[PDB]
Amino acid sequence: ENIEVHMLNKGAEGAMVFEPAYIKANPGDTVTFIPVDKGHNVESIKDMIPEGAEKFKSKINENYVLTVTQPGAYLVKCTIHYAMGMIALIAVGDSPANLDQIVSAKKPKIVQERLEKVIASAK
Ligand SMILES: [Cu+2]
């Protein structure tokens, strides 16, 4: 199945957000990122995707279809607005083995707070 995600300048959680910011998917699903506001992209974060997965980076303002195969958790960002907290978490399959590692990893304090809300007030 397909899961559609919007990239927005402003949303429920504030400025520069992905909606939804928590995405549950199964191997073989697709995640479609739609730039409803311009100035955004999607890129996988170094060491914050499962082992075996390839990294990716889309073009600014492009509609991007991501096919997820390897199970685990994926933290993705908007390259442009990562420092302002623009991130989304994709969880592929149940009990993603690297999720605690991702939560502990080093990242901007604004992104850390949003990530904690996605796993709490999101799952
Ligand atoms: Cu952005």
Image (cartoon, rainbow, N blue to C red):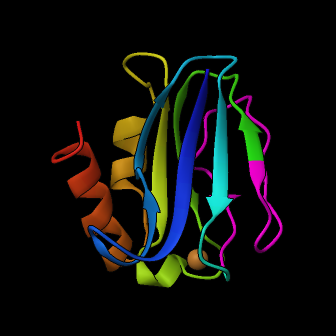
Identified at 23% across, 43% down, the residue is 122
Give the camera-side residue of 87 and 46: 87
Question: Which quadrant holds the N terminus?
Answer: top right
User: Is 85 situated left or right of 119 in this image?
Assistant: right
Determine which quarter of the picture holds residue 31: top right
Identified at 47% across, 71% down, the residue is 86
Part of the protein shown in magenta: 40-64
Residue 49 drawn in magenta:
yes
Vertical comparison of 93 with 122: above or below: above
Identified at 78% across, 74% down, the residue is 60
What main secondary structure does the magenta stretch of the protein show? loop
Determine which quarter of the picture holds residue 78: bottom right
Vertical comparison of 89 with 67: above or below: below
Where residue 29 sits in the image (x, y, percent)?
65, 23
User: Is 11 situated left or right of 39 in this image?
Assistant: left
Rendered-image quarter of ligand 1: bottom right
Vertical comparison of 2 with 57: above or below: above
Q: Is residue 46 visible?
A: no
Identified at 40% across, 16% down, the residue is 94
Residue that lies at the very extreme toward the left in this rendered image: 121
Where residue 19 sits in the image (x, y, percent)?
43, 56
Determine which quarter of the picture holds residue 62: bottom right
Question: Which quadrant holds the C terminus?
Answer: top left
Q: Is residue 109 visible?
A: yes
Give the camera-side residue of 107 and 20: 20
Give the camera-side residue of 12 and 115: 12
User: Is 77 situated left or right of 118 in this image?
Assistant: right
Residue that lies at the very extreme toward the front in this rendered image: 36
Where residue 112 sits in the image (x, y, percent)?
32, 66
User: Is 23 situated left or right of 123 in this image?
Assistant: right
Where residue 107 sits in the image (x, y, percent)?
43, 70
Residue 110 drawn in magenta:
no
